[PDB]
Image 1: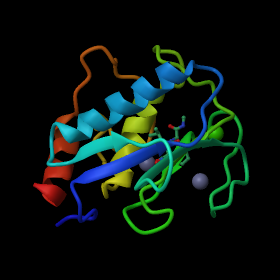
Image 2: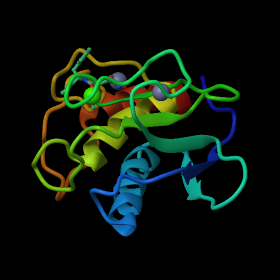
Image 3: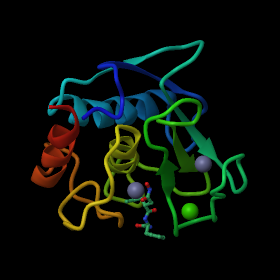
Length: 158
Ligand SMILES: CNC(=O)[C@H](Cc1ccccc1)NC(=O)[C@@H](CC(=O)NO)CC(C)C
Ligand SMILES: [Ca+2]
Ligand SMILES: [Zn+2]
Ligand SMILES: [Zn+2]
């Protein structure tokens, strides 16, 4: 049963981490959504101005919700389940080291986990699953969604 009632969702990258170029940030975020798109009927589009279903941002410590960030390591990011207002948004701890390599922490794998939340998935007990609550570098190169996450997206949207 769908958390999101629409299949064509929009996203907006609110600010960027200065640790990567803007293009590098945009590609990691896009690659992250396409992972979920190939296993479900959902399609993602970026917008420049206005209201997006999914807002993405980099914040430091207290940022206006109930979950303040905690500096380097510890919690890396958080996301809200489908809803109105903050629902669907993904927040990244600006105090982390963000990369696009195997070095901690790879933005693409962190954003791919957050987006599962954004779409309605919960955490997974399978350590090989992207929805697992502990970060692990897997690869990036020919990374495709693990089996457990396909089962989880398919169970909600077909
Ligand atoms: C190096 N840090 C971690 O692996 C911590 C470990 C942890 C787990 C529970 C409580 C505190 C810390 N995990 C997270 O930051 C996760 C928080 C979360 O689930 N967002 O949606 C996100 C990763 C899976 C990408
Ligand atoms: Ca942190
Ligand atoms: Zn937040
Ligand atoms: Zn999570």
